[PDB]
Amino acid sequence: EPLAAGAVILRRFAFNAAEQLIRDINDVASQSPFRQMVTPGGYTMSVAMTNCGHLGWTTHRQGYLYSPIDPQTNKPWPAMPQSFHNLCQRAATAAGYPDFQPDACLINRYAPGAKLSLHQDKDEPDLRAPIVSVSLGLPAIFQFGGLKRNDPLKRLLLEHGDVVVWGGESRLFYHGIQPLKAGFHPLTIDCRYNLTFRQAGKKENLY
Ligand SMILES: [Fe+2]
């Protein structure tokens, strides 16, 4: 029996691909800079973000959505790097999702003390498609609950190279990241990067 129904934890799965993945995060950031987006309550997120791929998650007039254009540059988000595409496919396939074809990758950067409040990934057209998570750099405590608010939370440390394929029931769980502890990592220096691959466009975009 699993810790999270439908989730597939692949520890250190991206450990070897880590250095290249980071070079690509930096490349993506040179075009679409990391920016701290504004929350519903008007607060600035402590986590900094950016996207790559055809679609990118962002804020838009009191709402949140996937856009083919970066509002900060008025240009498309950078294309999905080969390292990203490859790693995701290998993880998705190993987890039993060979047809998963993400068109969006939200890149999160956590500086010491950065955290992500509880939320569900429900902005995607088809929730049967999983979300592949890739952690890099400083370790973080990932928390997840259930399908509804105020449900009992479970914690899980996510470390450098860890990949989790959130499929099945786990795909809809409320989740977040507790305040990042300060520290040092050879490849990221003083932060943690997290990539979350999503199939954000409707199936028609595949034809
Ligand atoms: Fe999320």
Image: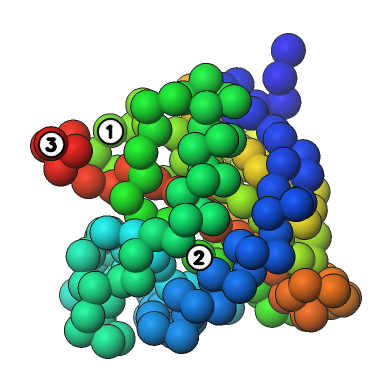
* Marks 1 and 3, how far apart at CA: 16 Å
Mark 3 — residue? 207
* Marks 3 and 2, how far apart at CA: 26 Å
The quadrant in which the C terminus is found is: top left
* Marks 2 and 1, how far apart at CA: 21 Å
Examine the rendering and report whether any part of residue 119 can be seen: no
Mark 1 — residue? 126
Q: Classify mark 3: helix, strand or loop.
A: loop
Disc 2 Cβ-to-ligand 1 distance below 8 Å: no
Q: Name the front one of labels 1 and 3.
A: 3
Instruction: State whether residue 105 is above or below residue 187.
Output: above
* Residue plotted at (34% across, 65% down): 79
Apparent side of residue 82 relative to residue 143 in the rendered image (left or right) = left
* Residue plotted at (32% across, 50% down): 103
Mark 2 — residue? 107
Apparent side of residue 126 relative to residue 144 in the rendered image (left or right) = left
Q: Classify mark 2: helix, strand or loop.
A: strand
